[PDB]
Image (tube, each protein chain N blue to C red):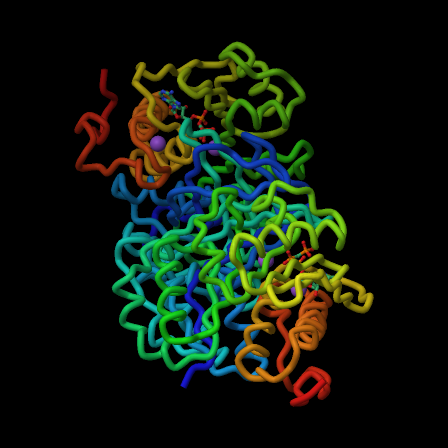
Length: 314
Length: 312
Ligand SMILES: Nc1ncnc2c1ncn2[C@@H]1O[C@H](COP(=O)(O)OP(=O)(O)CP(=O)(O)O)[C@@H](O)[C@H]1O
Ligand SMILES: Nc1ncnc2c1ncn2[C@@H]1O[C@H](COP(=O)(O)OP(=O)(O)CP(=O)(O)O)[C@@H](O)[C@H]1O
Ligand code: NA
Ligand code: NA
Ligand code: NA
Ligand code: NA
C-alpha cells in the first residue's frame, strides 16, 4: 500500500546550454544538450519516495520513447507505476529549456499527455487513492481532474495536499474547501489574492485571505525565509524560518518541500505542523545546495537522523 | 550501388508550437510538441531518395534513442545507413525550435555527434564514394571532414555539390575550388560576398564573385523568385522563375531543391542545367505547399510525369 499518492504531472526536460539566450527570429548554437525528468507531480513524489515513503504516481504520459523513459525514471526512484498511464493521442508532456552560463533561462512547457489523464483513469485509481494517507495534487493536469482527485480523497477521509501551481487567479471554490493543506509560493499567493507577497508579513495577510476561502491549513513558502503557516484552529500566522545555506540552484525547491511535507503527514502524523514544516524546510534547503531539480533531492541515508525521530526534537 | 552520397548532418528537431515567443526569464505554455527529423544533409538525402535516387548517408549520431530513431528514419526513406555511425561521446545533434502562430521562431542547435564524424569514418566510405555520381556536402559538420569528402570525390571524378549553409564569412577557399556546383541562398550569398542580395540582378552580381573565387557553376536560390545560375562557360546570369504557389510552410525548401538537383545531376546527366533547375524549382515549390520539413518532401509517384522524362 502506497501511503502517499500523487495525482499529477510528469514532464520530459529537454535542456540546451548556450552562452547567450536567443531572441525572436535568431538561430544560435549551444554546446550541450541533455534530457532530464521533471513535472511538479513527479518531483513531489520523488522527494517523498527518497525520504522512505511508499508512493504511487497517478499520471499519464505518451505511448512514446519519452513516456517509456519516464516510467523507468519512476521505477528507479522506487515509485509505483501501477497507475502511470500512456496515450497514443498526445505526446509526453515537455519542458523545453534554454539555459545560459549564468543560469537564466527560457522555458516552453507543453502539457501534452498530462491533460488527457481523465475520469476513467481516476476511477481505475480509486482504490489506491482511497487507501492512502495523503493525496497530493497540483495544477499541471486538467484542473477538473485535480478536483476529482481531491473529491475522491475527501470522500475517503484521506488527507488532501493541494499545490495550486502554476496558479490560476480564480479557482473553483471547491479547491479550497476540499483542501486539508493548501500550499503555495509567494508568486502564486500574489495571483490568488491580488496582494503583494514579498515578506513574511505580507504572506500572513495573503494566507488569511486563502484560509477564509475554506482551506483547513494554509502554507506559503518564502524561499530563503522559510514558510508561513495558518490554520482554522490557529489562524494567527507562524513564521517558520530556515537556516541560512549557500544556494547553488533553487529550482524545484517547492516541490522538494511539498514532497517532504507529504512524507511527514503520512509517516509522522503525530507531529505538529510546526515540526513538520521545520523538517520540510530543512530538506528543501538541502535541495537548493545542488544543481538539477530531481537530481538534487536528498535521500534519507544522506540526511541527519534527527529528521526521522518520532517525537518532537529541540 | 549508391549514385548520390551525402556527407553531412542529422539533427533531431524538438519542436514546440506556441502563440507567442518567450523572453528571457519567461516560462510560457505552448499547444503542441513534436519530434521531427532534420539536418541539412539528411534533408537533402531524403529528397533525392524520394525521387528515386539510390543514396548513402555518411553521418554520425549518438548511441542514444534519438540516434536509433534517426537511423530508422533513414531506413524508412530507403537510404543506406552503411556509413551512419553512432558514438558514445556525444548525443545526437539537436535543434530545439519554438514556433509562434505567425511562423516566427527561436532555434537553438547543438551539433553534437555530427561534429565527431571524422576522416577515418569518411575513409571507410571510399569505395562507395568512388562509385557514386554526385557527392553532396554542407557546413553543418566539421570543416576538415567535408573538405576531405570533396577531395575524395574529386580524386574519383565524382561530381561535387556544395551547399555553404549555414554560411560563414571567412570560408576556406578550397570550398570554392573543390565545388563543381556551388548552391546557396540570398542571405548566404550576402554573407559570403559582402554584397547586398535583394533581387535576381543582385544575385547575379554575387554569383559572379563566387565564380571568380574558383567555382565551376554557381546557383543562388531566391525563394519565390526561383533561382539564378551562372557558370564558367556561361557567366551571364540566368534567372529561372518558379510558378506562383500558395505556400503553407517554406521550411526546408532549400534542402528539397539541393536534393532534387543532386538527383538530376546523378540520374539525368544529359539534361541542361537550366532544365535541371526548372525541375528542382518545381519540386521545392511542391515542398512549400505542405507543413513540416522532411514530411513535406514529395515522392516521385506523387509528382508530374514530365519531371522524370529523359529530355527537355
Ligand atoms: N535560498 C534558500 N535557502 C534555504 N532554503 C530555501 C532557499 N530557497 C528555497 N528554500 C526552501 O525551499 C522551500 C520552497 O521555496 P519556494 O517555494 O520559494 O521555491 P521554488 O520552487 O518556487 C524556487 P524556483 O523559482 O527557483 O523553482 C522554502 O520554504 C525553503 O524551505
Ligand atoms: N514561396 C515559394 N514559392 C515557390 N517556390 C518556393 C518558395 N519558397 C521557396 N521556393 C523554392 O525553394 C527554393 C529554395 O528556396 P530558398 O533557398 O530561399 O529556401 P529556404 O529553405 O532558405 C526557405 P525561404 O526561401 O522562405 O527563406 C527556391 O529556389 C524555390 O524553388
Ligand atoms: Na512550487
Ligand atoms: Na536544487
Ligand atoms: Na538552404
Ligand atoms: Na514545407
